[PDB]
Image (cartoon, rainbow over all chains, first blue to last red; front, side, top):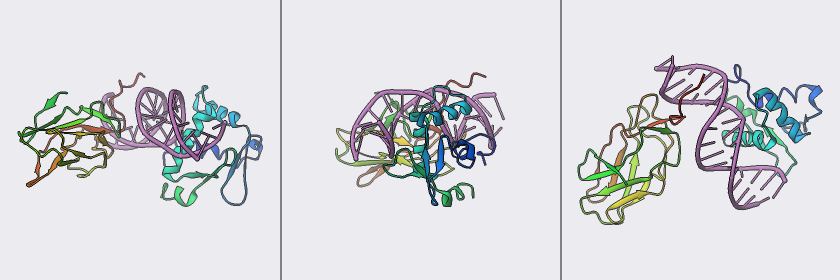
Amino acid sequence: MPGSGQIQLWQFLLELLSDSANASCITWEGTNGEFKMTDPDEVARRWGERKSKPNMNYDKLSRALRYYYDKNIMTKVHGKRYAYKFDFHGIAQALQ
Amino acid sequence: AELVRTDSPNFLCSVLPSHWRCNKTLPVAFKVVALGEVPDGTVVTVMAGNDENYSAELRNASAVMKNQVARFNDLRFVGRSGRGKSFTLTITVFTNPPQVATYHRAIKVTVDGPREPRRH
DNA sequence: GAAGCCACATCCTCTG
DNA sequence: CAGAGGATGTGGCTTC
């Protein structure tokens, strides 16, 4: 599905969780779906590096992620410093 | 504002543009005119008609007749028509008896409104 | 290939 | 100040 040919966020963001060598900027937080945010403005930077969008910041990338709520991809861990989580039991009806 | 003909010559409505994007603040809000004397207080709803998906999703779709001129705070078109395809939107006036004017080729509902096309 | 999609980019606003 | 959110252009990508 169109995640294959053209690069995504959630498809991209999890090139950095799974890879041990990028924990400089992120990490899995616990057994259940969660994720921490190391440098809030080095993260956005590399998403600029891929998207060819040098003006990129957190505010920009972040908004894109907050769309995901209404579509049931991922969701927010309330009041936690820059931490959301993935909905997989829905990613598979969204790739059914 | 500017008006256009109908399939009931007793009522008229706004010039809704050729082609627009899914769910925008309309460039000109929707006026619906009563030439025949209508009790100012009667309700008016619209239903987007098309051989494909004969009932599309709409918002602020119901409005109230006032001074023989029913206006829609801001109507918005969500449910898409398709490629090259427009809506024959139906227009209901809740009275005794209620009356409708069909309206063919009203507006084309796509993802992009017609942006000046690509520069590649 | 313009015409419909798509999934961010960018943006300026509130309100928790 | 972060975070949810409307509006609106943008660029890549299937479909006629």
